[PDB]
Amino acid sequence: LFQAEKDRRVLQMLRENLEEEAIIMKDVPDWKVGESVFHTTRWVTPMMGELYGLRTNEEILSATYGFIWYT
Amino acid sequence: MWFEILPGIAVMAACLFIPGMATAHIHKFTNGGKEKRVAHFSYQWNLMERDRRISGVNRYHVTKGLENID
Amino acid sequence: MFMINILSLIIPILLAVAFLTLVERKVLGYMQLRKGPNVVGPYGLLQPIADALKLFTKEPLRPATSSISMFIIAPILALSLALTMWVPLPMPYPLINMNLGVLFMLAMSSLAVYSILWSGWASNSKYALIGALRAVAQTISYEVTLAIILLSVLLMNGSYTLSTLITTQEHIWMIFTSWPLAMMWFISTLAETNRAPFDLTEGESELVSGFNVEYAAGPFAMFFMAEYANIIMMNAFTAILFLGASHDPHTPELYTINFVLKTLALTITFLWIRASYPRFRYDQLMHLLWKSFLPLTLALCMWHISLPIMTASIPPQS
Amino acid sequence: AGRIASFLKNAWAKEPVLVASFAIGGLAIILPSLSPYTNYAIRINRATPYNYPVPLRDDGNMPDVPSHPQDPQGPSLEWLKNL
Amino acid sequence: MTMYIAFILSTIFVIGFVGFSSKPSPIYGGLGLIVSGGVGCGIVLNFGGSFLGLMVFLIYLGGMLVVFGYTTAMATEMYPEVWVSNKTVFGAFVSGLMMEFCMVYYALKEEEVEIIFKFNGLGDWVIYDTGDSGFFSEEAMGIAALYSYGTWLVIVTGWSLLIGVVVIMEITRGN
Amino acid sequence: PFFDVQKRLGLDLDRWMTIQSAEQPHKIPGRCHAFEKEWIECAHGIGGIRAEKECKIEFDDFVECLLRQKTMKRLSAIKRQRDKLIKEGKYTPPPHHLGKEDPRP
Amino acid sequence: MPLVYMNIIMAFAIALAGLLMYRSHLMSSLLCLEGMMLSLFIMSTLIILNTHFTLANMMPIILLVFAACEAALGLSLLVMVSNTYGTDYVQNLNLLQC
Amino acid sequence: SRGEYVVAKLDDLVNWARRSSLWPMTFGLACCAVEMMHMAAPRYDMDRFGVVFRASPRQSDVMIVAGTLTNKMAPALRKVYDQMPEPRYVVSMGSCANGGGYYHYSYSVVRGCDRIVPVDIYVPGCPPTAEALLYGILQLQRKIKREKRLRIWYRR
Amino acid sequence: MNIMLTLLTNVTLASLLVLIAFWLPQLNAYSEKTSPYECGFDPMGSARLPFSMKFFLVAITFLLFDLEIALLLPLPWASQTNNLKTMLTMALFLLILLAASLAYEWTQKGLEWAE
Ligand SMILES: COC1=C(OC)C(=O)C(C/C=C(\C)CC/C=C(\C)CC/C=C(/C)CC/C=C(/C)CC/C=C(/C)CC/C=C(\C)CC/C=C(\C)CC/C=C(/C)CC/C=C(/C)CCC=C(C)C)=C(C)C1=O
Ligand SMILES: CCCCCCCCCCCCCCCCC[C@@H](O)O[C@H](CO[C@H](O)CCCCCCCCCCCCCCC)COP(=O)(O)OCC[N+](C)(C)C
Ligand SMILES: CCCCCCCCCCCCCCCCC[C@@H](O)O[C@H](CO[C@H](O)CCCCCCCCCCCCCCC)COP(=O)(O)OCC[N+](C)(C)C
Ligand SMILES: CCCCCCCCCCCCCCCCC[C@@H](O)O[C@H](CO[C@H](O)CCCCCCCCCCCCCCC)COP(=O)(O)OCC[N+](C)(C)C
Ligand SMILES: CCCCCCCCCCCCCCCCC[C@@H](O)O[C@H](CO[C@H](O)CCCCCCCCCCCCCCC)COP(=O)(O)OCC[N+](C)(C)C
Ligand SMILES: CCCCCCCC/C=C\CCCCCCCC(=O)O[C@H](COC(=O)CCCCCCC/C=C/CCCCCCCC)COP(=O)(O)OCCN
Ligand SMILES: CCCCCCCC/C=C\CCCCCCCC(=O)O[C@H](COC(=O)CCCCCCC/C=C/CCCCCCCC)COP(=O)(O)OCCN
Ligand code: SF4
């Protein structure tokens, strides 16, 4: 159940980021929205810079340093 | 005594009483009164984050029972 | 609300140190067929307050030849380490729940001696230098034995988390399993905190107060506070490691009371040993630790590695 | 086998710490080989499920693979409950 | 952007390296190396390296103490030097600090390449993997695998330590 | 030079640690397991000289997984344009990117 | 590459220059060597942790071990130098020329 | 007024703190040092009054001149008195330290320690009994109690 | 974060104590007062002169021994491997090597201090 919820959450965050990038990148002349950086076409796990890239600082802090700093 | 040393020792004991219980009380007062969760590994942290997300109030200790699934 | 916890852990420890000074003075007096301080307050209860107020209202002195920055930094480092090494202790809930508490304690304890070293070097006096060298010899003698003893004891715990020591000995004290290691660890902690018969870094009869001979009023008081806080903290760590108490999750006050009583008993034992024996020699201490403690420690480390595999009793929490 | 007894006597009379340490080390070296409980420790270590057991795709030729956790097939930890 | 904790720690690391690398009377060099070791322990703590950081801190502290005793015995002078007691030491310290600050400014403002490759910046929080772990610790298992997988490493390490004891004894034999 | 005795005797003295995807304890995978495995399978057998020309795609993907230089460049460009737009005043980021998101388990 | 890696590389380069400068003493150069070991250790463990190379986590520790040996070796030599001159100054090591 | 009350109370507190805990420096010269030792004996137990010996001059409050002060020693006594941080007090014990005593006319005896250091309390005897020295210490405590530093500073 | 806050609080408290100790009392320092402390007279040499170390060899051996504990500390986690025989053999081998090195120092009069 946790695996299913994690997959859905990651996919939702990626879709939200892609939609927002499509909105922002509209006036850029030579930009392709949602373009992969890998020559392959399989699934590559996100980097956490791609999930919480456009979000606030508190969410980023909880995402990256949340577990290590919890004591 | 020889028992005249007992007062001072007692006072010292009182001082050593103060931290421990206080910490416990603080933990309870900060976590709904139920022994603040321990997250030694990543799985327990993930569980805590899931509880915080589904709580609806941004507090991991606000647990939801069977009444939250209709 | 965390700062409240920090203050509630800091202030009572300092008060306990202040009253431990009076308790030690009275205990030594009564073991020396006299009374000890009983004049300043009722049964001498106000003596530490008068001592502290006198020390902090007295002129602080800095030597002309002394290196200033180290001379001032050393007491700050000593007191800060003494106060910091209290957080990971479970009583029964630690303030900071570290995954590796024992290693953190070892590293901070190793860093603590640098306060003594730097104070002795910056004082720029011969007695202070001799005291610093004696401290170096002492730590060289005891460090490896202390670390191996800790590892051998924790081999039956399964991890370095201090909270797991509470549930490891839920049924039986760990002193009934490793009492030779218990005795060796007790001697090692006696040598670690610079206490009699291993109080060579001060050497009142030999080095006229030793490394802190040049610290007049305030920093000397801070050094005294750091030493006594280290004494109490090491005794509490020994009590938790070897004499585990029963912890009921719905009433931690019972565990707190038991742990405090055990710590006080160990501290009184420390004062007893100080009053009972003469002083070692700083080469004889090294010879004792390297010719009598290291072989037994290595043998018991091998034994405690083999025993869980031999009897199929490996602890959980890989 | 006669002079070794005298040497042990002298070592015990003069340096008992070395004798005790050597005896403990030797016991720790030899005893685990003869102990029948080492295999039990290894089995207990192997029985700890740190990671998820991935199910196998059924090709119709797996008689020893259970179709459900409560099926009688597969490894059993009944020996552990009695230890 | 995220409190620059790792960046601040790295800057303090480099500052301590500059402090002890200008060779100011090894007592202060030892202090600088202790500061650098502690800050590096913190840096690797921030990345999940608990055991490794604590081990390097302890090993260095023990090592530094031996060094302090040795400089007191053999490497002391009547007027020990400090970062402001000599023109050369101060010059080296200031040059190191200034060049570190210049590199930091150039990397933060621009994607400048100095020696290896171009600079990115934008904090080091980005590279952290989103993958989760189990009930075990990845570093703890990797280190503990030394006794089951690294038999060869253990053998060569033990032989090297024994030979090192013999070697220091032979060197300090004298004659 | 390289007196290879491991292959002669079949000892495996230090080959268990050479690559990232070779029997880690508890089956813990590397961050770039798939890319490294793909590159290794591509480059095995042809030789060193051919592996730098025919398996260049796999090596490039593996390096990109290792260092993520292209990903960080893309993210920095997106963030730069985003901050320029917010300074100009046409973006108005959505609530779920500001802290008003409805979280899901 | 993030700023942390470049800062560690800068620390290693600074320590290398400090070792190669040889001001007056011999203890200071040994301290520079140990600083180089420390920077190597920190960079290696950062790289290992970033890529989740599990089996390589034991690599830094072995590093540290040999570092100790090196340190010990240097200290031994220093003692002899002192016992020949009463001072660890490098200016005294000039009996052999090129 | 209000300030006068505050300074009086603060001065009383500081005087009590300094009086209750006096730390004499371990410093004896001659016969009178044996009686100084006997003051620390279980019968009298000066420690119970807060008076405990400390070796280093930097951590000392009171200097008790117990014994004859010869010409060879006078620079050392002045040196160890100078190194005591203020406030510091001197108690002169015995006739030898008071005014020379039995060796007043000798060629190598300083006729009283008051020529070298300022003295607060003079304890007479040869040697003064441990009770006499305890009484002198209590008189020094009373003298410290009578002192008024902050009150004088306020009226400046 | 919590550990950093604890360290900052402790350091601030110690610094405040030092500041109060150095600024509250009346300071009257003259040249004779701040002189170096010998027992009663002036020091002959200097405290910065070389101070002979009679246990240098023991110090170097401590340097080498301090890494044995670093190698041996992951044993509680190494106890959880599947093949316990190899782990036990390697741990015992390392401890035997440490004991052998200590014995070799002992017999060759390496632990005795210099005269
Ligand atoms: C015959 O031939 C001769 C000799 O041959 C024998 C001689 O020898 C000789 C020279 C000898 C003479 C000079 C006489 C010497 C006397 C004897 C030899 C010995 C007499 C006594 C000895 C020294 C033995 C003493 C031992 C006892 C057990 C006494 C106890 C020992 C103490 C040192 C231990 C206690 C330590 C002190 C009391 C200091 C403790 C005080 C603290 C530092 C203060 C508390 C800490 C605070 C800072 C806490 C602050 C925290 C706060 C929060 C608290 C609250 C404060 C707020 C305001 C609320 C002569 C002259 C001689 O002719
Ligand atoms: C959250 C709870 C934590 C508890 C922690 C454990 C216990 C800590 C308490 C420590 C006990 C200290 C011993 C007190 C013994 C009683 C002393 C009392 O009987 O004597 C009185 C002492 O009175 C003092 O005022 C009491 C001081 C005790 C508190 C000091 C402890 C330090 C911590 C807090 C300091 C704040 C001090 C505030 C009051 C001045 C008599 O003095 P006084 O009545 O005057 O007479 C002289 C004035 N005349 C001449 C006009 C008559
Ligand atoms: C940092 C927080 C604390 C700050 C400082 C407070 C420390 C705690 C205060 C301690 C209180 C105890 C002081 C007095 C105890 C009573 C003892 C009484 O007997 O003293 C008498 C009188 O003492 C003084 O009159 C009392 C002094 C107390 C002054 C009150 C000040 C309150 C503290 C205010 C601090 C901050 C003020 C606000 C501005 C910032 C004289 O007795 P004495 O002759 O010797 O001994 C008799 C000997 N015998 C037994 C043999 C016969
Ligand atoms: C227990 C832990 C918690 C404690 C919490 C409280 C923390 C207390 C902080 C520590 C300081 C208290 C010490 C008490 C005395 C103050 C020391 C110093 O700050 O005062 C004077 C510092 O002042 C300087 O002399 C000159 C000051 C002129 C510059 C003014 C400061 C800038 C403000 C601008 C003026 C505007 C109005 C100021 C009032 C708001 C020292 O002068 P100095 O003679 O050397 O030293 C002798 C002090 N004696 C007399 C007490 C022995
Ligand atoms: C063959 C050449 C002989 C002449 C050359 C001699 C010089 C070299 C010294 C000895 C060579 C070391 C060879 C050991 C290679 C390790 C591989 C093999 O031995 O199996 C190991 C078994 O090791 C055994 O314990 C035996 C090795 C113990 C060696 C005893 C030490 C004495 C060596 C002599 C030199 C040391 C210094 C001097 C000592 C006096 C582990 O197997 P296993 O665990 O299933 O698989 C691990 C992988 N898993 C976890 C995925 C399953
Ligand atoms: C069936 C398989 C079982 C396997 C074996 C397991 C059992 C092992 C049996 C042997 C155990 C012996 C343990 C002894 C520990 C070592 C002590 C030692 O040998 O050193 C002493 C020295 O010890 C000391 O002198 C230390 C003095 C310090 C005194 C401190 C206070 C006295 C004791 C206080 C109470 C002790 C409390 C211990 C527990 C505290 C609670 C944790 C001898 O040295 P020397 O006499 O100098 O001889 C060398 C020259 N020939
Ligand atoms: C391969 C098996 C190894 C496993 C067991 C060992 C594990 C670790 C224990 C050993 C630690 C290192 C020991 C170092 C030995 C040094 C010996 C030495 O040279 O010291 C002699 C002293 O030692 C001796 O007397 C010579 C050897 C004494 C006997 C040593 C052990 C012999 C066998 C004992 C156990 C036998 C088997 C157990 C039987 C138990 C009874 C049934 C010199 O005397 P000093 O103290 O330096 O100076 C005295 C003058 N001031
Ligand atoms: S006064 Fe009398 S007893 Fe005291 S030192 Fe002089 S001669 Fe001796």
Image (tube, coloured by chain):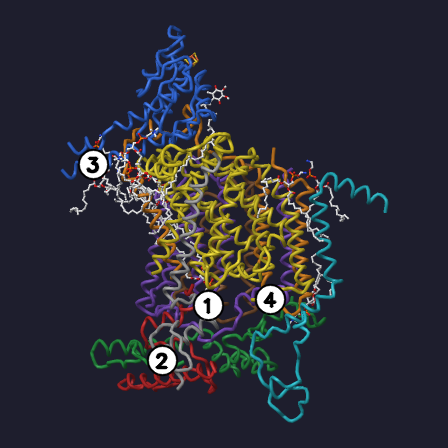
Residue H7, which numbered label? 3
Above or below, G73 against F18 in this view is: above
Chain E's colour is purple
Work out whether residue E33 or residue B14 is closer to the camera in this orientation and state it: B14
Q: At x 28% / y 78%, what residue is drawn?
A: F81
Tint applied to chain I in the drawing: orange
Contact check, label 1 and label 4, Cβ < 8 Å: no
Chain A colour is red
Q: Report the mark closest to the observer, 4 or 2.
A: 2
The residue lying furthest to the top in this view is H105
Which SS class for mark 3? helix
Quarter of the image that includes the C terminus of chain D: bottom right
The brown one among the chains is G
Shade of chain H as shown in the rendered figure: blue
Image coordinates of residue I68 in percent, x first then y, are 60, 54
Residue at figure coordinates x 75%, y 41% from the top left: D11
Q: Label 4 belongs to which residue?
A: E145
| In this rendering, position of residue G49 left or right of residue C312 | left
